[PDB]
Structures are given as structure tokens and as C-alpha cells.
Length: 53
Ligand SMILES: [Fe+3]
Image (cartoon, rainbow, N blue to C red; front, side, top):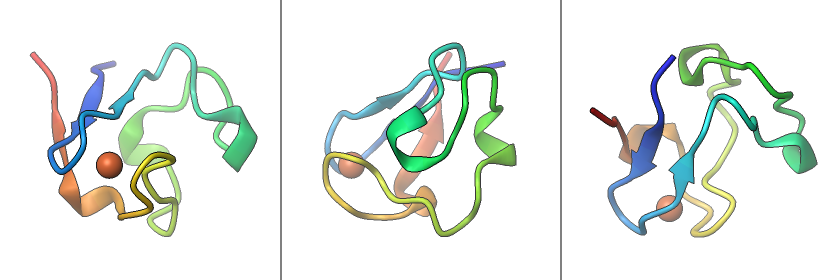
């Protein structure tokens, strides 16, 4: 699985760590995250994210 980052703010989603405070457990592929989950830092949605390489 790949990290994704928010291209509006730098927030890196790391699949290893999930985002547990918002319901996304460790091991959750970004593409498996609920499409109504927001960047925990800027409060925008998945669509401002891109795959990291
Ligand atoms: Fe963001």
C-alpha cells in the first residue's frame, strides 16, 4: 500500500498507521477509506489527495 498526501496541505496519510481517531484503522488502503473521510489537518476530502511514490 502507498502513502497518499494532501496536495492542499502536506498531510500524509500512512496506511500503516491508518487514521484511528476518525475511524480508519491501521492497514486501511486509502482506496478503502470512506469517501466522506476528510483530511484531519485541513478538513478537505479525499479528492485533494494523491498517491505518493
Ligand atoms: Fe489537507
